[PDB]
Image (cartoon, rainbow over all chains, first blue to last red; front, side, top):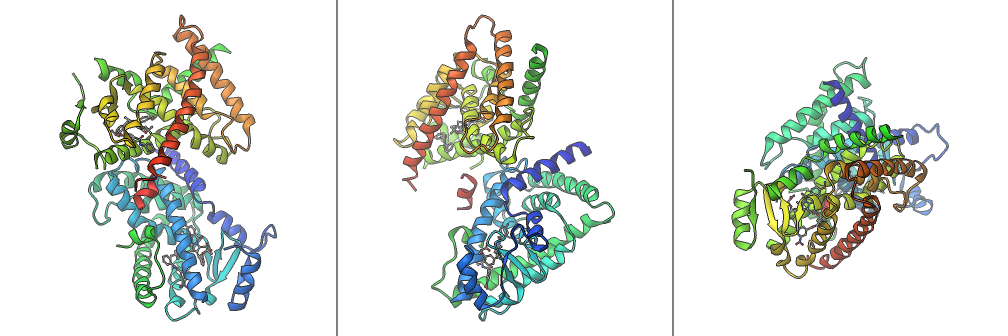
Length: 257
Length: 250
Ligand SMILES: COc1ccc(C(=O)n2c(C)c(Cc3cccc(O[C@@H](C)C(=O)O)c3)c3cc(OC(F)(F)F)ccc32)cc1
Ligand SMILES: COc1ccc(C(=O)n2c(C)c(Cc3cccc(O[C@@H](C)C(=O)O)c3)c3cc(OC(F)(F)F)ccc32)cc1
Ligand SMILES: *c1ccc([N+](=O)[O-])cc1C(=O)Nc1ccccc1
Ligand SMILES: *c1ccc([N+](=O)[O-])cc1C(=O)Nc1ccccc1
C-alpha cells in the first residue's frame, strides 16, 4: 500500500537530514555560484592551497590524502548513525549489522560524495572550499588518481539528478544488501530491502514522473559503485607499501578486510 | 476540554501499543500468571540459557553489552513513538533530536520498570527472566549497574500504573522544555502543557482513589533524571576497562 511506502520515504528522509549535515541540497546551493550568501574559496594549484590554509579551516599530496581519511572516518559515523534509524536494522543479528556496515559504508560514501562533486571538482571543508579535479589529478605518483575515478562515477551518477529524498531510500537499500560476504541471516535483510526497494520505486516514480525507468537506471549504478570501491582498496595497499610512516585509521582499517 | 484529552489519551495509548511490542500488561502477566520464561539465577543457568534462548551478540561484559543492544532498539521504539505525539514532527528538527537525545534514557528506565519485579528483570523480549540477585552477583564494576534500576522500579511500580497511564506519561518526558540546547521551547511546552492536562484526567479517571498520583508521578521524574546521571557516571568508571561495533553503541 502506497501510504506505508510513502510513510517510509518520509521517515528515511527525516533521519537522512538529521544524520548528514552536508546534503546535496546545500551542496548544489553552494555549487551553483549564484548565491553570494557564502561562495567557497577555490584551491586550484599549490599556491592557492597555501593561501587556502589562512582563511579556511580544514608535503602536500599526503596531507590531502589524510584529509579524505579523516572525513571518511567522520562519514562512517554519520552513515552508522543513519543505519540505526532504518526500520528493522538494529533488530538484526549484531554480526550482520556489523557486516552490512563493513560493506555498505564505502558505497554510501562515494554515493554521498557525488553530491559534493561536479565535473570540475569537489566541495571540501563542509563546503568552505572547492578543490579542483585537475589539481587533485596532478598530485605525486600514486595520489593523482585517488579521486579521479570518484569524479568519473559522480559525473555519471549525478546525471540521474537525484535529490536528497531519493538518496535517502537508496543509501538505505545499499546498507540492506543480503549478498554481503559472511551474513548469518540473509533473509531478514532481504525482507527489509524488499520494502526499501518498494519505497524507492514509488519515490522515484513520484519525484521524477517524466523520468522513466530511473529506478532501473539507479539500481544499475551500483555496479559502478562496487568498481570504485575496489580500485580505491588496492590503490590504498600501494600507499601502505609506499609509505609505511603513514597510518590508516583503526575504524577504516576494520572496513577494509 | 475533557473529551479531547480523552481523544489525546487514546491516541497515545493506541500509538504506544504499535511502537512497544512487550507492554506492561503483557509483562505483568508473564511475571505472575502457560507461557513462563527460562530463568537465569547463576552462572550455570546462563550458559544453558544462551543455548536455548534467541539472543543477538567474559560473562559480565556480555550481559552489559546485551543491555546496550536492547537500549539501541528502545531508542528506535521511542523515536517511532515520539513521531506520533501530536505536534512533535512539526517541531524544529534540531529540537526533535535534542528532546529524543535526553528523553530517551528516562523513557528506557520507565519502560524497564515494567519488566522488573523485586526479584529480577524480564529479559530477551520476555523469553527469559534474569534474577536480580545474579546481576548483583556480577563483578564490582558490573554488579552495581542494574541495582539502582531495580531500586527505582520497585518504587515506581508501587504506583500501579498501566500502559494507558504510561502512554501519556512517557510523552510528557519527551516534551520536556528544559533539555540543553532547545531553539524553540514555546511549542514544546505547549504540547507538554497539553500532555500533562491529559495525564491529569487519565490518572484521575483511571486511578480515582489514588489521590495526588499526578504529583507522585511528576516527582518520579526527578528520580528518573538522577538515574540517568548515575548511569552516565557509571559508564565513566567502566570506560576504564577496555570499532565498527563501537560506532553503533555511541
Ligand atoms: C558518506 O558521506 C560523506 C561523504 C563525503 C563527505 C566529505 O565531506 N568528503 C569530502 C568533501 C571529500 C573530498 C576531500 C578532499 C580533500 C580533503 C578532504 O578532507 C577535508 C578537508 C574535507 O574537505 O572534508 C576531503 C571526501 C573524501 C572521502 O574519502 C573518499 F571517499 F574519497 F575515500 C570521504 C568524504 C569526503 C562527508 C560525508
Ligand atoms: C521501550 O523501552 C525499553 C525497551 C526495552 C527494554 C528491555 O528489554 N531491556 C531489558 C529487558 C534490560 C535488562 C537486560 C539485562 C540483561 C540483558 C539484556 O538484554 C537482552 C536480554 C534484551 O534485550 O532484553 C537486558 C534493559 C536494559 C537497558 O539498558 C539500561 F537502561 F539498563 F541501561 C535498556 C533496555 C532493556 C527496556 C525498555
Ligand atoms: C582524498 C583526497 C586526496 C587524495 N590523494 O591526493 O591521494 C586521496 C584521498 C583519499 O581517498 N584518502 C583516503 C585514504 C584512506 C581511506 C579513505 C580515504
Ligand atoms: C545491562 C545489564 C547488565 C549490566 N551490567 O551488569 O554491567 C549493564 C547493563 C546496561 O545497562 N548496559 C548499558 C550500557 C550503556 C548504555 C545502556 C546500557
